[PDB]
Image (cartoon, coloured by chain):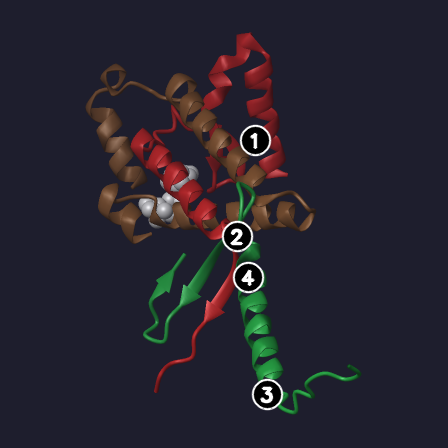
Amino acid sequence: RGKGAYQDRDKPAQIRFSNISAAKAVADAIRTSLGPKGMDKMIQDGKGDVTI
Amino acid sequence: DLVAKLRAFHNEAQVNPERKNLKWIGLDLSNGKPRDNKQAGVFEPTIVKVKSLKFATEAAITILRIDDLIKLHPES
Amino acid sequence: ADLQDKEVGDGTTSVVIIAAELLKNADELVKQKIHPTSVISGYRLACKEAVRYINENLIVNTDELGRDCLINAAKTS
Ligand SMILES: Nc1ncnc2c1ncn2[C@@H]1O[C@H](COP(=O)(O)OP(=O)(O)O)[C@@H](O)[C@H]1O
Ligand SMILES: [Mg+2]
């Protein structure tokens, strides 16, 4: 048996890691606004409109 | 000292049932002394104070509810 | 301030000053690790009790005074 498939291509692993990192970043960003003790966020658009 | 004297007057009015007439003690800005503002002719509509309190409380609650700001850059 | 002007017409500076002071003190409490929800609940209860106390103890009926009450209110304005 010995070694298996070499998997010379490393790009798929990097793509998976980047996707996971982005999803985790989004989840962490919106984590603070969960539950009865969560707090709102204020978002200002490019047009200058504000929403809470 | 003026605010301290006013607070003392109102505290005495609240704790002593025999001095309930001190509730009207306000500020006389001309001489800088506490003065009975009911007999001095300094009145306001009650709706002014009530609406001011309600609106200010709601605005403070609305602002205090924020803990994070995202400011997107203008498209141009 | 604009809403206070539209709905009442007087006390436009007082409401802004009171709101700013309320916000400043609330943030001072929050900096001491007091949760903002507790501060909001306390503010709501305090506002309700203040309104009740004003309506029950600090009001003067105008019929007791007459046109002098209107004149004094205008002059104060
Ligand atoms: N003759 C007076 N003596 C003492 N205080 C007064 C007198 N007239 C008005 N005030 C007080 O000054 C405060 C400020 O009122 P003002 O700023 O003129 O109204 P607004 O906030 O609508 O501009 C009022 O809360 C009122 O109680
Ligand atoms: Mg005024």
Q: What's the amino acid at mark 1?
A: Leu
Question: Callout 1: 10 Å neighbours few (<14), some, many (20+)?
Answer: some
Question: What's the CA distance linking mark 4 and mark 1?
Answer: 53 Å
Dot label at residue A33: 2
Q: Residue furthest bottom?
A: A8
Label 2: chain letter: A
Q: What's the amino acid at mark 3?
A: Lys
Label 3: chain letter: A
Q: Is residue B36 above or below residue C12?
A: above
Residue drawn at point x = 60 percent, y = 72 percent: A21
Judge: label 4 CB < 8 Å from ligand 1: no
Measured from the top left, where is residue C27 in percent x and y? 59, 50
Dot label at residue B6: 1
User: In the figure, what tint was chain C given?
Assistant: brown
Label 4: chain letter: A
**Looking at the colours in the rendered structure, which chain would you say is drawn in red?**
B
In the picture provided, is A33 more to the left or to the right than C3?
right
